[PDB]
Amino acid sequence: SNADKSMELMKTLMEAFGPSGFEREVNAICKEYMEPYADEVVVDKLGSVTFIAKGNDRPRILMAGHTDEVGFIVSSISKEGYLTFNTLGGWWSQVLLGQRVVVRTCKGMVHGIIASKPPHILPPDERKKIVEARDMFIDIGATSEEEAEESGVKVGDPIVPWSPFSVIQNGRVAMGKAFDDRIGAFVLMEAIRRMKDQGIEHPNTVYGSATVQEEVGLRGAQTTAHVVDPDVALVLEVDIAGDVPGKPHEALTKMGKGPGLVTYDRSMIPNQPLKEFVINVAKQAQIPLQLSQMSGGGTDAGRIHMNRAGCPSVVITIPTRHIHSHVGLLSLKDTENAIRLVIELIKRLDLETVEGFT
Amino acid sequence: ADKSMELMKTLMEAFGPSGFEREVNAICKEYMEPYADEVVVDKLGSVTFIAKGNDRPRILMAGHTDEVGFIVSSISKEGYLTFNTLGGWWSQVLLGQRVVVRTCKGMVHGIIASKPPHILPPDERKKIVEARDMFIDIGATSEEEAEESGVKVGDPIVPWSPFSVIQNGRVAMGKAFDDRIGAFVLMEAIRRMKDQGIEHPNTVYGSATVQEEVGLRGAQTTAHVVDPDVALVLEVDIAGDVPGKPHEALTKMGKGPGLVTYDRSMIPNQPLKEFVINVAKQAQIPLQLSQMSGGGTDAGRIHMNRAGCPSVVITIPTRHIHSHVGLLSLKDTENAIRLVIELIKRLDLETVEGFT
Amino acid sequence: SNADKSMELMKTLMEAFGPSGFEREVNAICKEYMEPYADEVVVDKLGSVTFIAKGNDRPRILMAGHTDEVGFIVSSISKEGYLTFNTLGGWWSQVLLGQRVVVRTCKGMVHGIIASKPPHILPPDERKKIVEARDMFIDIGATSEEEAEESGVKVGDPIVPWSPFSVIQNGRVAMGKAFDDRIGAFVLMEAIRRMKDQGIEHPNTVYGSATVQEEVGLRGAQTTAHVVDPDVALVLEVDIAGDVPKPHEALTKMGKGPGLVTYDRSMIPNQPLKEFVINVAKQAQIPLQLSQMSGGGTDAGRIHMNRAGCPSVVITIPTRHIHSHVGLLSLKDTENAIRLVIELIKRLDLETVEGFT
Ligand SMILES: [Co+2]
Ligand SMILES: [Co+2]
Ligand SMILES: [Co+2]
Ligand SMILES: [Co+2]
Ligand SMILES: [Co+2]
Ligand SMILES: [Co+2]
């Protein structure tokens, strides 16, 4: 069953180990799923894998979703057997304490807990203070520097959140980590798969790219854009979903009310003709679409749209609750509609339409 | 063999926050059916297992089976739950954590959440998020969709935290060690005494108390039922293995069970304290002298029962208690079991009267 | 007449003098009203009176409502004729200034006003500061320490708010002091009265108790629980009503029915008993508001811990502005609380009660 194989892919992706800089396990999963569906596979030297579905040489459509997740890296082993760490990507410190993580050593996976000094051994005026991430560490159950070393831990070893994947709300809502942005990778992979399976023709060549190192500076996007030389780009990301009580204007999108379209973000102002194109394609296809704006965040598009002489680009999003944290939620219905939408766009992105954007 | 570890796993994974301990105490009753001579209860929900011997002295061993948790305080119009805490929680360990709510329709999963910091003014992002301003997200999109899951005000909530063993079988990881590990010890002590026909000049009341984390409530009522002549309370100790100091948290995980020499709720009977120290030394069981400047135990109530009851707290050092996931040493646990057996062997009427 | 006699009782209770430790006048009023309705009267040595309506020896149902009210006590007489005072029970300082009080001396009632230093004789930076209760005093119109003494005042003399009882909103809403928790006492007394008057049978013995010293540490509840040895307890209290323009911190609304407390700082209720009350209310079509008091306690905090434990639940009348000179509550809510408690008592037989534990 394909619905099984899809959900099995989703589960495997969200449960895979792949923080920024260490995405090889996740991109291997992507290659394997796509062996029977991509006409060719190209890579960048940072570790981004890109799947090509052939059609007309031009225009080249780049779809990108980053497979790196926010994570950590071992910065030292203390004499008592605790690990210090640096963050990989943007974390809010207040979601870290008490959380389970797993470190990948040469000897395998080692489990631990993010910890700090307990407040009752601090002065009364220091207990009301937020604990900064610089003062946290990871407890792996070791009782000495040696016992810690026996587990295989070395400075520079990568760390991810520990967070199992499941579905809740009677099959409607997915729960787990790394939705940002493996759900975007999931969408582009499923789009390409479906186009082949149902023989859907498209007047263009599609480059579906699982980029690396987005969360640390849009690094894989820059190098993948160089490799591809795209004529138009659809970046798939998550949107911060403002479903939480308290205003509306800072987070327009709601989980379950359809994919989002980003009208402005700190890294890019979208091409306006292309924006209007997506809005219309969605309206015509009756796919609900939420206009969104990310005042203080960026995307792979920030680099892609600046490739060579420029590249018209838009960001399309799945509203997700609690990103950049151990566990988030998103709607499977929104995801499905994002897949539908992207297919409809690709169907209609011929050379003439694309030249009309510039 | 598997049976002990299967019990440990089942206990630490059971649902049982303060006031709602029935599932956990059912697990205890079932494990102990073949080992206890009799079972008495208090009306709060504490179950107590009796291993018979001489009418007097009565030895009370107690470990509380309630865990810190939460309770649903409302459903917001958008489908989020507000909650009150059950027991003492540090707010800084809450955000982003998985919980599970027990409704009339079954278990409902959720995540502790707050307003995201990028929707707040710059000066409010550096502020700690207080628990009063948090809520639980269960994936609902409206007050109704939330109601469909079965949630009602007053429904109990626990942390979601699987049990496993790490460090090559040496260290247990999970929730609710405080104080199901204490319950685990007293149950295993009673089991072993029966299995190996170990005689004891006394009657032993092994009690799985309720509602410790909210005010030592089950201990008071269980003490009334039992009328104990001496009490051994089993608890966890906050383990100071974390970098940065020593004097505020004397105990270390893996260096043996602890003996509490002073806490906010009780100053132990001194003869009894010396007795335990000697029994441990003689039996070659490592024992860490401990002091909990700002915490209490079931003993706080037990030792005040009727005319008084000599009592002492014996502890397993545990890292990260009152949080979703903690760690303790299986070796320490084993030694706590050994120690308690040796004590019970030697607590005859004469020794016990000599404490007072 | 009975509706008159009821309202006359309500008025008399809310207007009676009875701060924590000095509840004798109010408990006398209760004894008098209940002479013709209780089968027996037992007391504790703190001053709690308890009225027994006989039936089956067991189970024993304890209903409790405290008759002490928040108040004050004279802590000194200043050389200028002003009184300093300590609080009896929890008061918010911001509701005290400018308020009328009455002090009970050996010579009788002496009226006064809570006062402080006026802000225009303070430095500019001290006027924006809240006046703490420690810096307040009571003005009784005296001009010297001697003129004050003539009124009969002594250190240790009790003080209550001055606050007449009336009904407003076309007879719907009661206004006055001490609703916490004389309204609870009113309910249990009216329940017992009505059960006798209408010959309503109940498979149990009912102990209706007017406890003392709740507001200073649940003191009368502990000692009354000892005397009674109850098998199940229904504590009647007020609920802070959140009708003022944070829904989750104060769930209850005045006029939307009695409340049922699902959690409070002093007790987590027995769960079977909680479900029982919810169902009895639903079946009897009595509106019932699920409530939670994150930072307050009740007589139940002590009662449920008596001996081996006692399953208990708190039932509440939503009241606005408790622990202040004047509050409001709904007579309709009160009536429904009386109805509810009767329905519960009817159904609390030995078998049901043993099923809670
Ligand atoms: Co992203
Ligand atoms: Co991101
Ligand atoms: Co404990
Ligand atoms: Co505890
Ligand atoms: Co009260
Ligand atoms: Co009060």
Image (spheres, coloured by chain):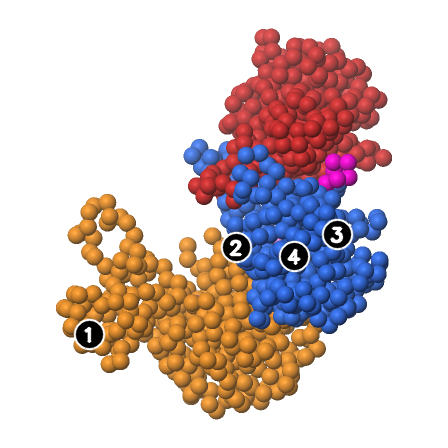
Chain colours: A red, B blue, C orange
Q: CA distance from mark 2 to mark 1?
A: 45 Å
Of the pair A324 and C168, the residue shown nearer to us: A324
Q: Is residue C87 visible?
A: yes
Q: Circle 2 sits in a helix, a strand or a loop, which is it?
A: loop
**For the residue marked with disc 2, what is the amino acid?**
Arg
Q: Residues in magenta?
A: B166-173
Query: Which residue shows up at 66% across the image and 80% down it?
Result: C349
Separation of marks 4 and 1 at Cα, in angstroms: 62 Å
**Residue B262 counted in the magenta span:** no
Picture disc at residue B338: 3
Instruction: Classify mark 3: helix, strand or loop.
Output: helix
Q: Residue furthest bottom?
A: C36
Name the residue that disc number 4 marks: B275
Residue A144, compared with residue B17, is above or below; it is above
Image location (x, y in percent) of residue C11: 37, 79
* Chain letter of disc 3 in the image: B
